Length: 182
Length: 182
Ligand SMILES: O=C(/C=C/c1ccc(Sc2ccccc2OC[C@H]2CC[C@@H](C(=O)O)CC2)c(C(F)(F)F)c1C(F)(F)F)N1CCOCC1
Ligand SMILES: O=C(/C=C/c1ccc(Sc2ccccc2OC[C@H]2CC[C@@H](C(=O)O)CC2)c(C(F)(F)F)c1C(F)(F)F)N1CCOCC1
Image (cartoon, rainbow over all chains, first blue to last red; front, side):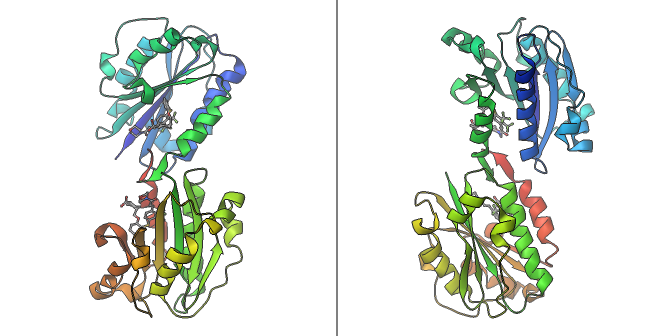
């Protein structure tokens, strides 16, 4: 039925300007494609700290991804993935910020680095979690494995390793082939 | 996996010019929303006779509903629904027209009247059939019932009756809420 979806995007220092924008363009592509549906969106940038760039209430008032993401500034710091998953779950998935109690919860994590913090993601056990690991930092099997503990299972379904930020376009192509009425 | 979908739309004399236009506009609204997906479309006008206005191969090459339908002329005759469905099954879902033999076949039938011919639609048994009945001709339970034999079962899932042609907007709104990735 209803799907409240949060994009949790990396704003670490490793990300070049163009790579950071390709993340934004990807999220905007998706949101545009799925306007006027049972989907509701929010977005949070995570580096060292966390910022709700816009929440569910904001999406419903605007329904305009371009406008909604126009204040994003690249944090340019670390990659605190654990703290960021917990921040989404405790501070973003809230009825007080437009979330629908009924809805299927989905989290899309987009990163170019291994996490710099630690802990657990117990607060997010009730959320379907996908993670996109992009670039050279994820060349090895071991690097790719570290990303599993953040995502739902199996990794074959919920973990996607992309070789470049151009490949975000290919992923948008792939997903659209999975868009169906019903 | 792939979905091959035909719009089989009514061009009977009973349709006023604006009503005919609104069917054309509904079809374009749907296709535009499902662009760049696993859906490929064909459109076929039926009254007394039948015409393929564009085929699947036209859609793949142009991906432009506006242009693909720009040359439709309202037939202004009868409503031979039986022969029309039969024309779709045997003449439209063909490699020659860009049909993928392995795909899921969908037929959307849009009509404002009861069928003027008879016979059977046994040739369309492999096709998932939806029928939209529009207007005052479908005021009675009885008249809406006459459409059941053309649609997949049950009628509650595959038959929709609309009071007016303006209500095509409302069906467009409803259907988009049923759009999902997966
Ligand atoms: O809405 C979704 C998921 C959407 C979704 C999922 C992943 C993703 S991205 C993703 C991340 C990790 C692995 C795969 C992924 O997608 C592969 C494609 C093709 C395969 C599909 C599948 O595994 O069924 C997924 C898409 C997205 C995204 F990113 F587009 F935004 C989206 C988004 F675009 F929609 F948001 N549902 C419904 C609830 O159940 C889960 C799927
Ligand atoms: O692609 C489709 C059907 C789409 C489709 C279906 C009906 C319809 S129109 C329709 C006609 C008769 C009854 C209902 C109908 O829609 C209810 C909505 C909401 C309920 C949904 C559901 O019961 O799953 C269907 C849509 C359409 C249409 F018209 F938009 F073009 C479309 C179209 F827009 F997509 F083409 N699939 C996926 C494969 O399995 C069959 C359904």
